[PDB]
Image (cartoon, grey):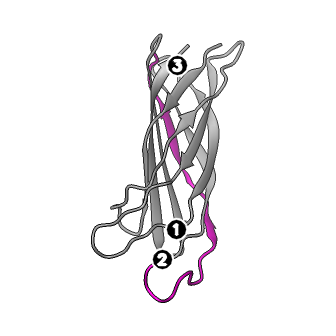
Amino acid sequence: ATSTVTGGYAQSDAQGQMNKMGGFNLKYRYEEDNSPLGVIGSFTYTEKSRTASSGDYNKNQYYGITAGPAYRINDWASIYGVVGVGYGKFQTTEYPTYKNDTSDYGFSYGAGLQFNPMENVALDFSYEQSRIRSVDVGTWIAGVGYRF
């Protein structure tokens, strides 16, 4: 078997891709004892706030669980479709309105991409998109790290 040890930074941004909201990442899955079959785990954690001069004071955190396998077509690369849900319950934490009416989910989906590994280097990507009504969310995650 193998364990592809990856992690890195992510930007979950919504309503207009402009927001550094990430924290850390770790991806860690097991590989099969016959086929070249792996599994691919996204985990996101958002713990950034964004001042400038307006008052975007990012309350709450997101939590986002997306999953799928990874398998080769013949023997070039291993990529697959991955699917999940994203839950965040934010609030405007400046203007005299506080939490308005927040609470919804979005079914995150996209593809999970995994690169040709090394003996101490891995390169893993997820790109997940969700919608809430008429606000898109996009989240990319870098999985850089090792493999053994």
The mark lying in front, picked from 3 and 1, is 1
x then y, percent, for residue 66: 61, 46
Q: With respect to residue 120, does 41 lie above or below? A: below
Q: CA distance from mark 2 to mark 1?
A: 7 Å
Q: Which of 143 and 60 lies nearest the eye of the viewer? A: 60
Answer left or right for 18 relative to 73: left
x then y, percent, for residue 84: 63, 51
Residue at horizontal 42%, vertical 61%? 49
Q: CA distance from mark 2 to mark 3?
A: 52 Å
Magenta residues span 92-117
Q: With respect to residue 148, does 17 lie above or below? A: below
Q: Quadrant of the C terminus?
A: top right
Q: Which residue bears the numbered disc 3? A: 74
Q: With respect to residue 28, does 3 lie above or below? A: above
**Tag 2's secondary structure?**
loop
- 3 or 1: tag closer to the N-terminus: 1
Q: CA distance from mark 3 to mark 1?
A: 46 Å
Q: Which residue bears the numbered disc 1? A: 59
As for residue 96 lying within the magenta part, the answer is yes
Q: Quadrant of residue 16?
A: bottom left
Mark identifier at residue 93? 2
Answer left or right for 33 relative to 88: right
The mark lying in front, picked from 2 and 3, is 2
Extreme residue in the bottom direction: 96
Extreme residue in the left direction: 53
Q: Main secondary structure of the magenta part?
A: loop
